[PDB]
Length: 75
Length: 112
Image 1 (cartoon, rainbow over the protein chains, first blue to last red):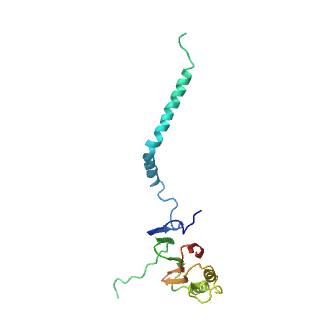
Image 2 (image 1 turned 90 degrees about the horizontal axis):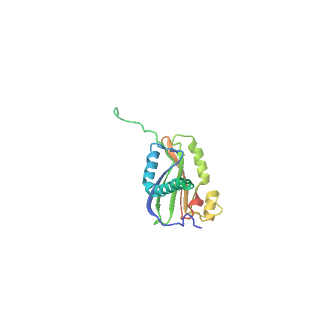
Image 3 (image 1 turned 30 degrees about the vertical axis):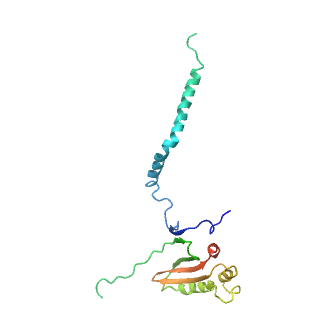
């Protein structure tokens, strides 16, 4: 495996941190959260949604058509 | 005298972390602390004792394995650092109580 101290080389980077007993677990959860999920969906819809609507229409057609196919009308 | 002499405000302790990472430097310095009571407090005496028990180390210390302090002993035997020091810095109504050390990049954990 691979171990801390022996991972990679990093220079000039200050991380500031805070103790969880000093800060909120849920901070601006709906204030900031809802704006993000919208933004993330907006971000991804045109890649994710179209194949599933493509499936949707092929499912509701294939259903409609299959059972209409097991019918006659004249003769 | 008469006009706009103010007393000191009390100082909020966070407890929190600052990590400034620089692998171009050959050894790590860590300094860890909990919050002290500061100058006035009778607790300083007792803390200073407990500190004294942990003590300090330096790689130039005479005779290593046999040091009283269990930190300093293990530090010396297992070459776990180059230096440590306990401390209790006092300010009015507050202070920093802990230790600081210096070591190799693969000692920082074991020393901790």
